[PDB]
Image (cartoon, rainbow, N blue to C red; front, top):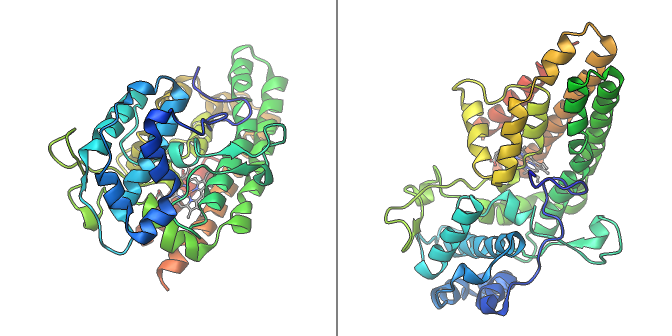
Length: 368
Ligand code: HEM
């Protein structure tokens, strides 16, 4: 369908951990990024790679793992240790297979949330539940970068959201078949699940250190669009002649908030305002099936107009409960951005303004 899993939602279920042996040289670099970046051997190892055909990656899961592998290597290659010594040309023997794979998966050739969070995890024990204690990431960048904590907590938020996402068909089927009680129950269930997702979001503090996120991890998630360090973009050697710009926005490419904006008829992509165009651009960095899901929801009849047309206080309160849970998520997200980016930075205003307008637009959708 739309590659939305009942249990893990937008996340990739049971991600592949190992590539075929043909790709051992890629996997070795990706698995040893902390040591290779620290010593300074990372870039030489990449420049020494043979060109490996992507022909031995034949299913979605091995393609997604290879994208995660190549994406981590690319971020490490471009940024190095993170102190201004950058590389402006990605060597052909990585760029060509990376771009070909990205074309097949319909994603930009840069590390994205769908790689480093949605595909970057495993269960320690397959017979135990999806808890931090029973999970790990597949790749990290530097020792002490809190990639395990940041990636896995984001993933646990996605998983919590899966419980609301799976109710969405019930919502549209109830509006269709005129089942008022069913719609009301479904909206309450969504609000309840979104409230639980907010509680899971609190775990960012349990597992992510602000200094480590801002000064280490954020470097490798950063991109080359409007970046003075790579003002023209990156040269994907042997694929495109001229450099191309792509955003590094892993920490804000989730489909979850936009999913419920569209569900609830909140028009965040409306107009030429900068917030709309930024949220529209983020979609290009989501998996195509998830972009298609978001567009399908926009094309369905409006949940908001349905609730507004019925003179039904119970329905309006269920709907408002959903909007308020989304407002609560975005408000806590603002707090997080303050603790993990702005405070460490000052020891910017466009970022917080963008986030506040998006929350404000959400808050304006309340009926009461
Ligand atoms: C340490 C934790 C986090 C930090 C520092 C952070 C940072 C940011 C930043 C800087 C942006 C602006 C766009 C960008 O620069 O990429 C953003 C937006 C966004 N973030 Fe995060 N983020 C964090 C955790 C999360 C989590 C766990 C989620 C959801 C699972 C999330 C979902 C979003 C979304 C959906 C947006 C788009 C704006 C919106 O729709 O309200 N973030 N975040």
